[PDB]
Image (cartoon, rainbow, N blue to C red; front, side, top):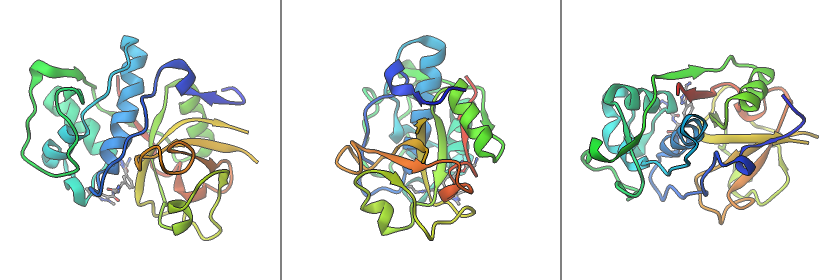
Length: 213
Ligand SMILES: *C(=N)CNC(=O)[C@H](Cc1cccc(-c2nnc(C=N)o2)c1)NC(=O)c1cc(C(C)(C)C)nn1C
């Protein structure tokens, strides 16, 4: 693992998206992690369908706009044998019936991995595998109103994490490079430098995973 990683400079990452008012952060988180692992194996970056996850991942456990888990999404992809592109299956910030069509699938996986709960373990996964799906405690107006700098909230938890995002790299005092799903208008062009190697700040390590590809 090096001193800094930016997986964006290497093709693994698509633009920042906006979840609307739907509470789907787990679909975005999970399509981003699948995005860069699909890039890894195939060398083509393709936008994936967050709506497909929202309408269809119920059987695995996700409650659409009421909530979900990244882990359950990858597990949908596995069980169902695919995900659709965003071309074919566009995002409507709304829960509806499943309109999956294999004739338009472009990603798949054989399950997921749960990274041990350590920041040293998180660093190394990011360093070797790609961007990783994580879950942090956004539950503060501080995070909501973040514009720029090394985000560090004095009263942030390490145990409960309410919001699933994407670690696309890290840098250097030191920071995790985090892609959110609240549009490019939020924070730093949609990204937020989260504090790194500080008693598991905002639980970023606590629940990191990625799709087996
Ligand atoms: C986003 N706008 C709304 N947030 C959620 O839906 C969160 C995201 C989240 C938080 C904490 C962990 C995870 C996650 N994903 N994989 C893993 C474990 N390796 O952890 C995702 N969702 C929840 O808080 C949530 C959803 C549920 C279900 C669907 C099981 C009821 N339970 N929780 C706690």
